[PDB]
Amino acid sequence: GSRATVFKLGLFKSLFLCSFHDITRLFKNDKTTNQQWVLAVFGLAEVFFEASFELLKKQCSFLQMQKRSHEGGTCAVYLICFNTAKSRETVRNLMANMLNVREECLMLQPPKIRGLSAALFWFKSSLSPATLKHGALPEWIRAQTTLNAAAA
DNA sequence: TGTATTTCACACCGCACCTCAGCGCGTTTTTTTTTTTTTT
């Protein structure tokens, strides 16, 4: 299982100071699917994180990732928006064949299309040095904080 | 009898359609002007 629990959320907050319930919202139904997803993964080495942008940036319309931390536990936060929708079990198997960790530290929920912080978080992350973007941002963030007149 | 594994089923919440009429809305030199021919 390990949909999204209080423990991962606590260290997520301790690192990026914004919740996972405020960037996504709720499904405990591990059957309901979606193409877009969010993810934060724990206990990762930076080399395979940089290679994670490498590997994933085949098959998704966008991909954002950012990294921490301070001597207390690493929370590599992803933003994943695949090409064809895949369930929490399928994307769970993908990422837990990706990151050489347990099924524990996965954070799978669809992103929330109406919400301010839900795109402010990634809009701030987009300027971070270790952030790795590919192509157009998904229409949710790329709707909430952008889609504004490029040159009036 | 306990439990993994999944669409229908009422609906959060909506992207975006069509639906009205109250807001904007316009031409005027040239001729005539008294000027000096214009018979006388």
Image (spheres, helix red, strand yellow):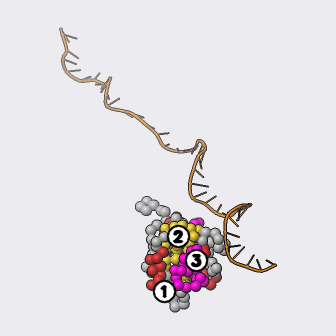
Q: Is residue A34 among the parts visible in the rendering?
A: yes
State the extent of the magenta-drawn residues as a range. A90-114
For the C terminus of chain A, the image quarter is bottom left
State yes or no: residue A133 in magenta.
Answer: no
- In this rendering, is residue A93 above or below B10? below
Query: Crowding near pointer 1: few (<14 within 10 Å), some, many (20+)?
Result: few
Per the image, label 1 sits on a secondary structure element best described as loop
Q: Which residue is mark 3?
A: A92
Q: Which residue is mark 2?
A: A81
Mark nearer the N terminus (3 vs 1): 1
What is the spatial separation of the Cα atoms under label 3 and label 2, in whole angstroms? 14 Å
Mark nearer the N terminus (1 vs 2): 1
For the N terminus of chain A, the image quarter is bottom right
Q: Which residue is mark 1?
A: A45
Q: Give the letter of the chain under mark 3.
A: A
**Residue at 61% of width from left, 69% of height from top?**
A33
